Image: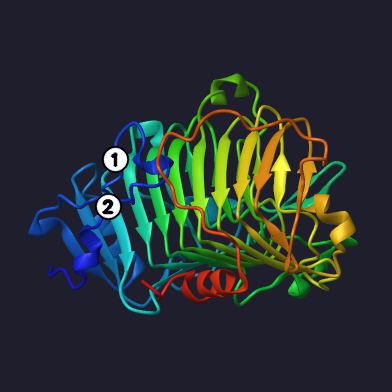
Amino acid sequence: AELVSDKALESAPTVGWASQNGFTTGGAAATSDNIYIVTNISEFTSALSAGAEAKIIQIKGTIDISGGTPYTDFADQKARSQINIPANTTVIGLGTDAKFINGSLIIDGTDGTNNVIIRNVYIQTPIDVEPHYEKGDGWNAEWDAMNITNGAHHVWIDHVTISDGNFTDDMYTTKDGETYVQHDGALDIKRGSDYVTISNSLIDQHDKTMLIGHNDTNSAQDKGKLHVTLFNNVFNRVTERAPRVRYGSIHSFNNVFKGDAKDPVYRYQYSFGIGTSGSVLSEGNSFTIANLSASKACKVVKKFNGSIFSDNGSVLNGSAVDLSGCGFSAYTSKIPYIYDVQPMTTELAQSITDNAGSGKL
């Protein structure tokens, strides 16, 4: 098909881990036969069947992963809603409304998948039709909006929006006397995945958001991997994990975090979660948290079994913050790429907010 957007051939920026130890070009080298325009789930999976061949898949309108048939149970949702994105693929949205609903985009390196670009698309978090009950935790949902796993590497997520959208948590029902949680994580990066860059994106209205590194049996294999760079993104009405990381090394700069500690649906808990062997370098980030005092600024970061966290130049509710005394160890590994961290002013925060998300490429 014809290439509508010339911007589709662009590779990841010089800044970011997705451009370290190799480049993330997606399907920039695709032949005309591997350039597609898809308007439904059938055309989407057909295009994806090109495998590792460089391919550019242009999304037009809303793609219903369920194909119009609601999932009847877990097995059904597992069998039909998880869409694998193969190596050397660029999934780019056309215009202002490229969207995915009722499913998950999976970047699974178990088959060697790498070099993937997901850009200018909106992904509504899936609703698990059959949450499983966990002894001591209650109902737990299984599916996320996007999952990077099993060693997938060199992934660039740009101008993407992930939101609970049409079904927010205040709409949850109850089953057997417990809140029937049907949303799981939003964006997960785990199991040895590496070299990822998340830019100009928006995650809006969601609880358990971004988990980098999962508590697995042989997690030591995550050591020295899961390097993720996040810049110019907006995390709005997100309860927690932006991200919560274990083993991975996160570089989060000039992002906007907006929430309310008394939000009636997505009550802000914290932004950065410092888990086992995880590290986070926060720079020039903007935190606008309603009902959060400057005296409790340390609440933007939460310590789990990890220790490494450093912040430089961030601001909370219009005033600069000093988190050096929050109880964490210094982030010392040197960032390998050149990057421009600007002072977090009211205007920068506004610009980031105005530009973040899908439909703004």
Please report contact status of discs 1 and 2: CB closer than 8 Å, yes or no: yes
Residue at 24%, 44% (x, y): give it: 51
**Residue 1 visible in this rendered orientation of the protein:** yes
- Dividing the picture into quadrants, the one containing residue 285 is bottom right
Q: Is residue 218 left or right of residue 147?
A: right
Q: Is residue 50 left or right of residue 292?
A: left
Please state which of residues 346 and 148 is positioned toward the viewer in this rendering. Answer: 346
Residue 62: mark: none
Please state which of residues 221 and 260 is positioned toward the viewer in this rendering. Answer: 260
| Percent coordinates x, y for residue 295 in the rendering | 89, 57
Label 1 or label 2, whichever comes before in sequence order = 2
Residue at 40%, 78% (x, y): give it: 97
Q: Which residue is mark 2?
A: 11
* Color style of the picture: rainbow
Residue 23: mark: 1
Residue at 67%, 55% (x, y): give it: 314
Could you say whether the residue bearing mark 1 is in a helix, strand or loop? loop
Identified by mark 1, the residue type is: Phe
Identified by mark 2, the residue type is: Ser
| Percent coordinates x, y for residue 168 in the rendering | 69, 73
Could you say whether the residue bearing mark 2 is in a helix, strand or loop? loop
Q: Is residue 254 above or below residue 248?
A: below
